[PDB]
Amino acid sequence: FTLIELMIVIAIVGILAAVALPAYQDYTARAQVSEAILLAEGQKSAVTEYYLNH
Amino acid sequence: FTLIELMIVIAIVGILAAVALPAYQDYTARAQVSEAILLAEGQKSAVTEYYLNH
């Protein structure tokens, strides 16, 4: 019944390859989001300039 | 599967070195343009003078 001990090791592996990964689709998003942040930044200038001029 | 976390960091780097640079060929232009602005300025004088005289 080391087999159990085995099947234990199996069992603990059994419920070890499921739901043990939080928030990574969450995390990639941030950067994937933040990528979008990276772009309109330059627009701020003429926006300011417009506000600056006007 | 920190490898994922790794490959995530890779992945987020993956789509991080592409299209994250707005409008700079746009911006250089302005000055590159504005350089051209700098020159004919002096012509305005005799232009005025011509208008001034005449």
Image (cartoon, coloured by chain):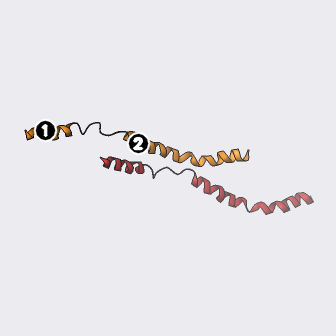
Chain colours: A orange, B red
Tag 2's secondary structure?
Answer: helix
Amino acid carrying mark 2 in the image: Tyr
Q: CA distance from mark 1 to mark 2?
A: 34 Å
Q: Is residue B29 left or right of residue B45?
A: left
Q: Which corner quadrant holds the N terminus of chain A?
A: top left
Q: Nearer the viewer, mark 1 or mark 2?
A: 1
Camera-nearest residue between B52 and B2: B2
Amino acid carrying mark 1 in the image: Met
Q: Say which residue appears at 86% left-offset and 58% top-offset.
A: B48
Q: Is residue B41 above or below residue A54?
A: below
Q: Residue B36: horizontal and vertical position, in percent?
A: 70, 60
Q: Are marks 1 and 2 in contact (CB under 8 Å)?
A: no
Residue at the spot of label 2: A27
Residues packed near mark 1 inside 10 Å, few (<14), some (14 to 19) or many (20 plus): few
* Identity of the residue furthest to the right in this view: B53
Camera-nearest residue between B46 and B30: B30
Q: Is residue B46 above or below residue A39?
A: below
Tag 1's secondary structure?
Answer: helix
Q: Residue B47: horizontal and vertical position, in percent?
A: 84, 59
